[PDB]
Image (tube, grey):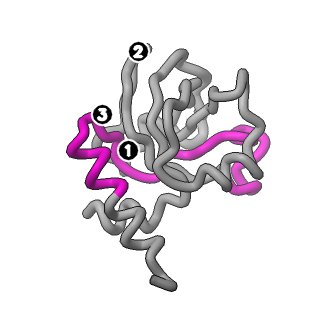
């Protein structure tokens, strides 16, 4: 469910796929260059852990991941991406990449509002 997906993704962002990158032969996945529009969660994590390209381009890996339902993209696609910075054990292959953690979501106000609500709910710890 969304609550779990949001909980397991330290970074959630919206963007459009600009280019399909290289395949990870060992893990059967591929990466893509994505132009970020807005961050719904974890902008600070990206800011401190990812070297952005051109100010708003990030490389997301993990596409094709057999364990993720909606895991494919084509150039021009726009989605809400649930990701986590690639851990070092995934380096060098995925160094500086955000890794897909769960299914890609379409850009609709409903999805935007719903994801934002889960992020906010979870953020509300003190409040």
Q: Which of these two is toward me, 31 or 6?
A: 6
Report x, y in % for residue 71.
36, 37
1 vs 2, front mark: 2
Numbered circles on residues, count: 3
Packing grade of label 2 (10 A; few <14, some 14-19, many >=20) is few
Secondary structure under the numbered disc 2 in the rendered image: loop
Q: Nearer the viewer, residue 8 or 110?
A: 110
Q: Earlier in the sequence, mark 1 or mark 2?
A: 1
**Tag 3 residue:** 107
Badge 1 or badge 3: first in the primary sequence: 1
Image depth: mark 2 or mark 3 in front: 3
Q: CA distance from mark 2 to mark 3?
A: 13 Å
In this view, the residue farthest toward the bottom is: 126
For marks 1 and 3, give the one nearer the viewer.
3
Depth check: 26 or 36 in front? 36
* Side of 88 relative to 74 (left or right): right
Magenta stretch encompasses residue 93 = yes
Q: Which residue is mark 2?
A: 76
Q: Which residue is mark 1?
A: 66
- Coordinates of residue 50 in the picture (x, y in percent): 73, 43
Of the residues under marks 2 and 3, which one precedes in the sequence?
2
Query: Tag 3's secondary structure?
Result: loop
Where 71 sits versus 127, above or below?
above
Location of the N terminus (image quadrant): bottom left
Q: Residue at x 30, y 33 (%)?
A: 107
Q: Quadrant of residue 112?
A: top left
Which stretch did the figure color magenta? 87-116
């Amino acid at each position: 469910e969304l609550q779990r997906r949001e909980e397991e993704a330290n970074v959630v962002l919206t963007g459009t796929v600009e280019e399909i990158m290289n395949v990870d032969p060992v893990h059967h996945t591929y990466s893509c260059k994505v132009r970020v529009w807005r961050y719904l969660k974890g902008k600070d994590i990206v800011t401190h852990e990812i070297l952005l390209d051109g100010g708003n381009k990030v490389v997301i890996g993990g596409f094709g991941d057999p364990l993720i339902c909606d895991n494919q993209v084509s150039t021009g696609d726009t989605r809400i991406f649930f990701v986590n910075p690639a851990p070092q054990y995934m380096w060098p292959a995925h160094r500086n990449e955000l890794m897909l953690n769960s299914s890609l979501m379409r850009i609709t106000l409903r999805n935007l509002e719903e994801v934002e609500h889960c992020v906010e709910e979870h953020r509300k710890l003190l409040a």
